Image (cartoon, rainbow, N blue to C red):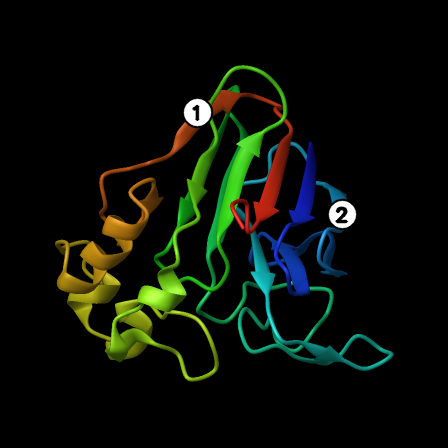
């Protein structure tokens, strides 16, 4: 499957793509404002994620840091990124269908649209100004809006026991972005697409 990753933000981002235990495609690349990078993701990829990283520095060997979304200091991510990270999430060719969503469960850094480029399903979007509006206690000093699990490490926020409800913090994310997951047990906003659809992830779709 192809995923065109498009940076419409006015700032550079370093796109990242992983399934947690391995890179997807090269795993990461710089995207200046306006650039597009198309990756190939193997059919059947389960639990894939794409995210943006901000304010990164890498040396000539690809090692460095980012303030949001850093994946063990690598340009080429093999592992998921450090929160806060808005997440485009997907599982492909699962009993004949693909499943896509956006999640704020690991916080929010950059607004995104995640849409098919092929027929048969709608896209999802979380493009509100979550960083600007972020509750004071969730603001990450390194940049972005942390989720409450990251900040407070409670069973309730982290949904450790599979027992949790919505919270004052989850509700903030849900108010700003109704179509993204705001906590682990949120009413799902996953979209079912035809198996083997192709996609576009757009950072900063609306400004």
Please indicate whether residue 88 sits to the left or right of residue 59 in the image.
Answer: left
What percent of the width, then of the height, locates residue 112? 51, 48
Dot placed on the residue nearer the N-terminal end, 1 or 2: 2
Instruction: Name the quadrant containing residue 51.
Output: bottom right
The local crowd at label 1, few if under 14, some if 14 to 19, many if 20 or more residues have their Cα within 10 Å, is some
Residue of label 2:
37
Looking at the image, which residue is at 72% across and 51% down? 34
Where disc 2 sits, the SS reads: strand
Looking at the image, which residue is at 50% across and 71% down? 82
Q: Is residue 109 above or below residue 87?
A: below
What percent of the width, then of the height, locates residue 196? 62, 24
Say which of 163 and 81 sits in front.
Answer: 81
Please indicate whether residue 91 sits to the left or right of residue 78 in the image.
Answer: left
What percent of the width, then of the height, locates residue 156? 16, 65
Proximity of marks 1 and 2: CB atoms separated by less than 8 Å: no
**Residue 102: mark in rendering:** none
């Amino acid at each position: 499957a192809t995923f065109e990753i498009v940076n419409r933000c006015s700032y550079t981002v370093w796109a990242a793509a992983s399934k947690g235990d391995a890179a997807l495609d090269a795993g990461g690349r710089q995207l200046n404002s306006g650039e597009s990078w198309t990756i190939n993701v193997e059919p059947g990829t389960n639990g894939g994620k794409i995210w943006a990283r901000t304010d990164c520095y890498f040396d000539d060997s690809g090692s460095g840091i980012c303030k949001t979304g850093d994946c063990g200091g690598l340009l080429r991510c093999k592992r998921f990124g450090r929160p806060p990270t808005t997440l485009a999430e997907f599982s492909l060719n699962q009993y004949g269908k693909d499943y896509i969503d956006i999640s704020n469960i690991k916080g929010f850094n950059v607004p995104m649209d995640f849409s098919p480029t092929t027929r048969g399903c709608r896209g999802v979007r979380c493009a509100a100004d979550i960083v600007g509006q972020c509750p004071a206690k969730l603001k990450a000093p390194g940049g972005g809006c942390n989720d409450a699990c990251t900040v407070f490490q409670t069973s309730e926020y982290c949904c450790t026991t599979g027992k949790c409800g919505p919270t004052e913090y989850s509700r903030f994310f849900k108010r700003l972005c109704p179509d993204a997951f705001s906590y682990v047990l949120d009413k799902p906003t996953t979209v079912t697409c035809p198996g083997s659809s192709n996609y576009r992830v757009t950072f900063c779709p609306t400004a």
